[PDB]
Image: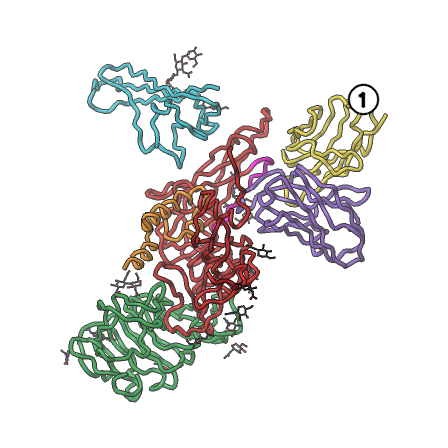
Chain colours: A yellow, B green, C purple, D orange, E red, F cyan
Amino acid sequence: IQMTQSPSSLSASVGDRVTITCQASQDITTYLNWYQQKPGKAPKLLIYDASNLETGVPSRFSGSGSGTDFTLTISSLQPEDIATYYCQQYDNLFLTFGGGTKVEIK
Amino acid sequence: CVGHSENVFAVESGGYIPSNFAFNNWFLLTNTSSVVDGVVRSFQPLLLNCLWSVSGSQFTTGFVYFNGTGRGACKGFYSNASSDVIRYNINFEENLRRGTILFKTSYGAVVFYCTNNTLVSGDAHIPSGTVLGNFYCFVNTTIGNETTSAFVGALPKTVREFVISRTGHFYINGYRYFSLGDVEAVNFNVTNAATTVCTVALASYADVLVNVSQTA
Amino acid sequence: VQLVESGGGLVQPGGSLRLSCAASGFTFSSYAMSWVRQAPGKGLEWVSAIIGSGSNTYYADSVKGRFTISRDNAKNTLYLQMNSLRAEDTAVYYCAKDTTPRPLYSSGWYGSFDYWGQGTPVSV
Amino acid sequence: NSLNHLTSQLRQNFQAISSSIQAIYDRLDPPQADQQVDRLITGRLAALN
Amino acid sequence: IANIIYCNSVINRLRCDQLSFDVPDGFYSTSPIQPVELPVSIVSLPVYHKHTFIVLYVNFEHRRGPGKCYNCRPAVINITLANFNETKGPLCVDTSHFTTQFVDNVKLARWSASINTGNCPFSFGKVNNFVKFGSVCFSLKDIPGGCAMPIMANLVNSKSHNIGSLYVSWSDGDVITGVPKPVEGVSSFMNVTLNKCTKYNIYDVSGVGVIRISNDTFLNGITYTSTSGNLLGFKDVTNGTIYSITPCNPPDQLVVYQQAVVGAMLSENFTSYGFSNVVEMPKFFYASNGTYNCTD
Amino acid sequence: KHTFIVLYVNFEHRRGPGKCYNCRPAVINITLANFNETKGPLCVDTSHFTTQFVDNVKLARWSASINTGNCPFSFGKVNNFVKFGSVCFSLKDIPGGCA
Ligand SMILES: *[C@@H]1O[C@H](CO)[C@@H](O[C@@H]2O[C@H](CO)[C@@H](O[C@@H]3O[C@H](CO)[C@@H](O)[C@H](O)[C@@H]3O)[C@H](O)[C@H]2NC(C)=O)[C@H](O)[C@H]1NC(C)=O
Ligand SMILES: *[C@@H]1O[C@H](CO)[C@@H](O[C@@H]2O[C@H](CO)[C@@H](O[C@@H]3O[C@H](CO)[C@@H](O)[C@H](O)[C@@H]3O)[C@H](O)[C@H]2NC(C)=O)[C@H](O)[C@H]1NC(C)=O
Ligand SMILES: *[C@@H]1O[C@H](CO)[C@@H](O[C@@H]2O[C@H](CO)[C@@H](O)[C@H](O)[C@H]2NC(C)=O)[C@H](O)[C@H]1NC(C)=O
Ligand SMILES: *[C@@H]1O[C@H](CO)[C@@H](O[C@@H]2O[C@H](CO)[C@@H](O)[C@H](O)[C@H]2NC(C)=O)[C@H](O)[C@H]1NC(C)=O
Ligand SMILES: *[C@@H]1O[C@H](CO)[C@@H](O)[C@H](O)[C@H]1NC(C)=O
Ligand SMILES: *[C@@H]1O[C@H](CO)[C@@H](O)[C@H](O)[C@H]1NC(C)=O
Ligand SMILES: *[C@@H]1O[C@H](CO)[C@@H](O)[C@H](O)[C@H]1NC(C)=O
Ligand SMILES: *[C@@H]1O[C@H](CO)[C@@H](O)[C@H](O)[C@H]1NC(C)=O
Ligand SMILES: *[C@@H]1O[C@H](CO)[C@@H](O)[C@H](O)[C@H]1NC(C)=O
Ligand SMILES: *[C@@H]1O[C@H](CO)[C@@H](O)[C@H](O)[C@H]1NC(C)=O
Ligand SMILES: *[C@@H]1O[C@H](CO)[C@@H](O)[C@H](O)[C@H]1NC(C)=O
Ligand SMILES: *[C@@H]1O[C@H](CO)[C@@H](O)[C@H](O)[C@H]1NC(C)=O
Ligand SMILES: *[C@@H]1O[C@H](CO)[C@@H](O)[C@H](O)[C@H]1NC(C)=O
Ligand SMILES: *[C@@H]1O[C@H](CO)[C@@H](O)[C@H](O)[C@H]1NC(C)=O
């Protein structure tokens, strides 16, 4: 079980609607989560069940899906975002994260 | 037992044990926990139908039933009805890990043996969590044209008395280890007889008040 | 809430390490836990897992036969007993804490983690 | 006789689940075992009285 | 608030327990603090041992669809009790040993499933503490005259929900016993620690005490008890050794004079309560800061 | 925050050839207000609550009532400032509770 995150890295400015698609290589149907990686920090939680905003983060993130097409998106990027994003599934005892993505200064 | 002809005594009229007998290797039967010192009242198998010796008797008794069939040459008062407890007596530091014990029920014969070598048992019940380098005992019931085996547990280095009830209760040194179900008869196949088994007593329950000291 | 790790360094292939982790501010004995790693400039992959009771442990396929996991519920400790490193164990480790609190006797599911410590890097 | 009467009061269940305080906590959860131990406490304080 | 006293010293502890700021001169009872890190000792009779697992499975399905709610109740709830079957009869145990394990297969995060005690004289998880039964049967369908165990589902810091039940019929007796698990070779027949206060369960009698070797040859029985019923000793039905059991903190007596603790009569041969001198009297040891340079 | 636990009791003696009284009635339309029944027993989640017992028993000579059962409290007496840590009501059994 794996998940492909593409594109690997994209540069974006303040206000754009950034998007990442986490291809979970198979259907899990709700068991997923997302994380925020500002460089040099331990990963922090962003989204769980692919739907629920972690209350330690502002509400400007969202994601949905049904199948393998589960996504994560930004409404309007705010300047301090410039971070890496990772997805994971929690269906199985053998849980495998994805390759990652980035939003970068511009 | 041994010497006196009283350690193998003559029971008085009515079935009472004489008031001067020292109760050497006669245990107080307990069911959860044993008393050390004190005075206790209990229903105990001490009313003797009739009591015979095996050591020095040359009879060996063959097989003993509850209803009086298979009695030895018992001395003193002898009652002629059915008992519900049979008591076998054992010598000084003698043990029973050198043979077999045969119970017989209305549903078939039931064997009881003990050996740590696995080639005697066959079906070994896989008793996990035990020390494989020492002895444990087993049971071998028969269904007539059929027979099954089971692991029962452990018996100590030293046995001093063995008591069996009509409803299957199985006591060693005063504690009930097993419950074998209803039985008709019992016989003690072990070698070096006439020394390993000292006396056999047919008895029934009665209300008694007992001095006990040092659990004896 | 506070989370911290300990025990990272540099050892020879096949050696041993006492990776450690400590926690404070929450009921340690009732939450599931899982060690997760990240090779330098690579993705994140699950390593090992443990439920609140500690009755069973779960291991990764490539990690099998090398590392084992345990805690001590008495004084809030958690470990990876490490053995038999090959070449590619170089990474940073995290004792990620599972969100769900579970009854102390139950064996239940797991796999979503709220808080991560400072991270502990190791190499072979 | 007074001491024997006092020591015999320790086998009383007092209609608690069991006469052993440790056995109650081995059988029941803390919010339920407290309501069972309280019977032994009240009964044995009566024995001392 | 007029004045306060911290219950930290030995004299203040006695004042706090006696619940008075002034304590008259005399001899007061006291018990040392029990150690909390307590090993476990188990002794049991080897018996006919077949073993079954009373496994309860709980998992409930959350409707994935239009309404993406999370703080609501799930759509469906299957509960199972392993080899149970409604059309053949209630399931229960004939083997001597058994264990109860609760499997919470709920997959959702920030979620859990639990079981309550209900009106039943024992908990589902506490059967693994060497409990006796004569016959006990479980069933997801009601058993008349039995006990009911409510099942729960809990969102963290949110209203909990009831999703089912579990009915148990019990008639306590000495035929079958619950154990935590069939262990991978570790014996449940003789595994004890010595000279350390431990929580024991020896021949199905449980408590806290200290186990020692003995000098007695008591022939009869395997468990020896006091009139109160407490366990004084036991025998290993192998070699036959006798062991003794004693509480790890027996009562002491403190001698108090002029609102200060001047001495202490101890059960054993040590310098307790901070005193630098201990002497042996005919029936107890006594510790104090005295020099025996006194006449009155 | 206030909640009304309103029990409704409506029943009728069967319309038909039997103009009976002393024998049992037939239709038992009891409704527990907000009880949608697919979302668990009605657990109150407001600071304050009160209970109402409304019957629409139109038949004369007939009356509706409730009985205490084994409950440590009564349906009509809960309004006397009785305290709970949680409370739920349901037409079907809520096993482990009181009836
Ligand atoms: C309600 O939950 C129960 C408990 O999990 C579900 O029953 C279980 O369903 C799985 C289906 O894979 C069974 O596992 C399979 O068992 C066979 C042997 O029977 C084995 O060959 C397969 O490899 C696999 O392990 C499991 O045994 C079964 N358990 C029981 C107690 O029936 C049930 O399907 C769930 N139903 C609904 C409608 O949610
Ligand atoms: C059983 O009894 C219940 C009440 O205990 C009956 O429900 C109630 O029926 C009346 C009929 O006049 C409803 O009045 C109207 O209802 C609609 C909504 O249902 C509303 O929009 C109207 O303004 C008006 O109030 C009454 O409200 C209704 N109760 C509820 C809570 O809706 C029911 O009809 C009886 N029969 C059966 C078979 O259930
Ligand atoms: C030990 O427990 C057994 C089982 O309860 C007792 O067996 C009873 O024994 C009496 C005679 O002592 C019989 O009349 C009963 O019929 C037996 N059956 C039952 C079901 O109780 C036995 O008495 C107990 N005591 C001892 C000392 O073994
Ligand atoms: C006492 O017990 C003996 C032994 O069980 C009984 O002996 C049986 O007697 C019948 C008589 O029809 C014989 O067919 C059996 O072969 C004997 N059985 C055994 C096992 O030897 C005896 O009948 C019993 N008597 C009383 C009065 O109870
Ligand atoms: C017992 O009955 C048999 C019947 O033959 C008899 O021989 C024996 O003497 C009887 N004993 C007594 C004491 O009645
Ligand atoms: C017990 O029976 C089994 C078969 O059930 C057999 O292998 C074994 O030899 C028997 N042993 C004795 C002592 O009867
Ligand atoms: C019993 O166990 C011992 C343990 O060392 C073993 O050597 C022996 O073969 C077994 N049999 C007998 C008869 O002692
Ligand atoms: C009784 O025991 C001996 C061994 O002590 C045995 O040889 C004999 O066969 C046994 N008796 C019967 C009837 O099997
Ligand atoms: C005794 O119990 C402890 C704790 O369960 C265990 O670690 C140890 O291995 C046991 N001893 C034996 C001899 O199995
Ligand atoms: C051990 O017991 C024996 C027999 O009662 C006794 O003589 C001896 O004094 C005891 N030993 C000790 C050291 O207490
Ligand atoms: C008590 O302790 C002292 C000093 O440690 C020692 O000399 C003395 O023999 C002990 N007495 C006993 C009865 O153990
Ligand atoms: C006893 O005297 C010693 C002398 O150093 C002192 O440390 C200790 O606190 C004194 N204790 C009491 C209770 O007087
Ligand atoms: C003992 O007491 C006397 C007074 O009663 C005192 O003078 C003396 O110094 C003390 N000490 C010794 C060692 O005699
Ligand atoms: C309760 O609500 C669900 C929809 O949420 C509906 O399907 C069901 O029929 C309702 N039942 C009742 C008795 O109102």
Q: Is mark 1 on a helix, strand or loop?
A: loop
> x and y percent of residue A60 in the render?
71, 24
The quadrant the N terminus of chain B occupies is bottom left
Left-right relation of F50 to B166: right
From the image, tell me which residue sits under label 1.
A14
Taking the spot 67% from the left edge, 51% from the top edge, the residue there is: C79
Is F20 or C119 nearer to us in this picture? C119
Residue range corresponding to the magenta coloring = E99-111
Q: Can residue E200 be seen in this view?
A: no
Between B70 and E198, the residue placed more toward the observer is: E198
User: How far across and down, in percent of the image, does residue E87 sit?
Assistant: 39, 44
E172 shown above or below E120:
below
Viewer-proximal residue among D9 and E264? E264
Which residue is located at x 74 percent, y 25 percent? A74
Q: What residue type is labelled 1?
A: Val
Q: In terms of image quadrants, where is residue B150?
A: bottom left
